Length: 297
Ligand SMILES: O=C(O)C(=O)Nc1sc2c(c1C(=O)O)CCOC2
Image: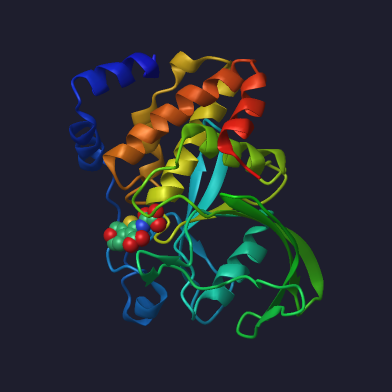
């Protein structure tokens, strides 16, 4: 079990070296388009880029570049798009991505402001009466409503492709108390948020991949995707002991660099997957306990 692994790791206390090891083994593939001079103002961090092979291409003639990747989990049969927090010049690209890729959900794990700094553009309308038009990629976006909980909010957004006037509804799941380079307050509130995204239908192979972002699209997003895929993998077979957590993080880092930013986020992933296995293994009663524990209202 991952659970025995956990206990070994904790008792020796070697999370850092374990994480060190993941970092040393992770793949390294080129990011030449991300590094082209034209794309400088499209990347938020110099040292966080999409790999060329897995990047998302915009369906524009101009410049198809966005800092986003498709994480395509073959065995689990689930994909996500991981991306950075949109910059002020790329919010139009971000929604073009959502449109072209046919996503139904956007999972945001950061606040706009963190640690004194602007981690992300305000890329969605905070009120119904004030829509956003993105003239560059010709899209319009309206808040339809939202559902504010103590640690998270769910918005319903209407996205319109102005050119054809086709519209779609996007669900936005905003986790607002997961610290940059930190962990959730607990596995319970993490799982509570994750199962809310799952319940909503957005992960569900009739839609495009869910878009997951934090500020860089690697630390908080990798943690979220790692726990989700681990639980999925375990569901298809009903076999916890077939899931190798480190190795699934390593399959994911084939598609985007840097997924999971610290050893305690790695450690939090084992906690999350070990708690969530109770639900996958057929005690659905823990779901309701997570919700209590989480203090959602
Ligand atoms: O938002 C996250 O969870 C995340 O991965 N962020 C990251 S990863 C990363 C940075 C940041 C940041 O927010 O400043 C700054 C550059 O180094 C790597």
